[PDB]
Length: 164
Image (cartoon, rainbow, N blue to C red; front, top):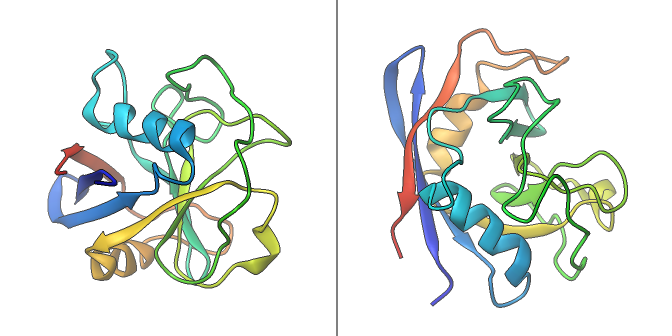
C-alpha cells in the first residue's frame, strides 16, 4: 500500500546486507515518490552504484549524492531542488528516513537514516519513511564512519529497487 524499496549495501565491494524502507506516500506523497523513483532508477538516473558519503556514529548515515559523491550534488526527479512538502512527521528514533538539505526548500536527492532520536531536526528536515527490515545492517554501516562524518571504507548501494 505504502511502497517498500530496498538497498543492498556493499562495503569496499564486499556484500554487507539488505535494508528495506517503508515510504510514507500517504503522508508525504511528493517526497516519497522522488525517493521511490530514484531507487528504481526509472527516470534514467538514481541511487544504484552511489555511496554513503557521511556517517556519524550515534547520529545518522547520509547518502544520495549520485553526481559528485561527496555531499555537493544530487538532483530530484522534479529538478535541482523542490520545496519542503510538510513537517507532519518527526524524528522519533532510530530507523527514520529524512531528507538532507541546504536550507529551506532545497530538497534534492540526499537523505539520511537516523540511528538515534534526533528531535532537534524536527521542522528543518522532511521525514518520509522508515527502515522496515535490516536496521542491523544500518548499525553495521554506522561502524565505518567517524565524528567528522568521513568513512573508513567505501559504503555503496550495490543494488536497489522496489519490493512493494
